[PDB]
Amino acid sequence: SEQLKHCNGILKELLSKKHAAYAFPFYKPVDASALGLHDYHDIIKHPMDLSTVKRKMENRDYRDAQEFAADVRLMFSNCYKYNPPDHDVVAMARKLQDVFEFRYAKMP
Ligand SMILES: COC(=O)C[C@@H]1N=C(c2cccc3[nH]ccc23)c2cc(OC)ccc2-n2c(C)nnc21
């Protein structure tokens, strides 16, 4: 749909080199074992990341823009839940979420 094309455009922007300096933590699922975050999956019940959003978009999983937005927002919320608010990753999440929200608001 037209709205899903807008969402795909947003997705491509979030993955683009333009935003890589602060988007990179969100590219792939959090590897909790790798990062030593042995409480991550006790605190975060529904992990989400941009590669998962991209797979869902490619597989036509999302039926509308609202479903797409809920997953992107879940990704950011997981970051805000797990990490203290002064953490560098939280600053990065806030910056990427600003990119997302401002462009999502321009939905046709
Ligand atoms: C040691 O990891 C952490 O304290 C949490 C982790 N931080 C980071 C993180 C991201 C950016 C700067 C950072 N400084 C210390 C940790 C950290 C992180 C890094 C990644 O690299 C592939 C992927 C995911 C995360 N991430 C997300 C998303 N949510 N929390 C994290």
Image (cartoon, rainbow, N blue to C red):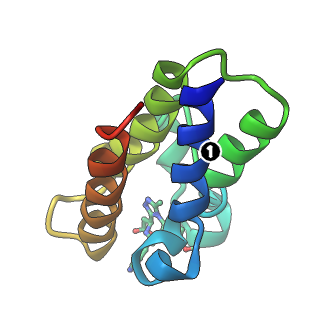
Q: Tell me where residue 88 appears, x and y as whole percent.
A: 27, 76
* Image quadrant containing the N terminus: top right
Query: Where ligand 1 lies, by quadrant?
Result: bottom left
In the orientation shown, which residue stands out farthest toward the right? 59
Q: Residue at x 48, y 80 (%)?
A: 18
Give 90 or 45, whichever is nearer the viewer: 90
In the orientation shown, which residue stands out farthest toward the top? 63
Find residue 12 and report its image quarter. bottom right
Give 53 or 31, whichever is nearer the viewer: 53
Q: Secondary structure at mark 1?
A: helix
Question: At label 1, which amino acid type do we have?
Answer: Asn
23 left or right of 61 in image: left
In the orientation shown, which residue stands out farthest toward the left? 86
Q: Residues within 10 Å of mark 1 (few under 14, many from 20)?
A: some
Q: Residue at x 66, y 60 (%)?
A: 28
Up-down relation of residue 20 to residue 34 (above or below): below
Q: Tell me where residue 62 appears, x and y as whole percent.
A: 67, 22
99 left or right of 54 in image: left
Up-down relation of residue 56 to residue 33 (above or below): above
**Label 1 sits on residue:** 8
Up-down relation of residue 40 to residue 16 (above or below): above
- Asked if residue 43 can be seen in this view, the reply is no
Q: Residue at x 42, y 31 (%)?
A: 108
Q: Residue at x 26, y 49 (%)?
A: 102
Q: Tell me where residue 42 appears, x and y as whole percent.
A: 49, 36
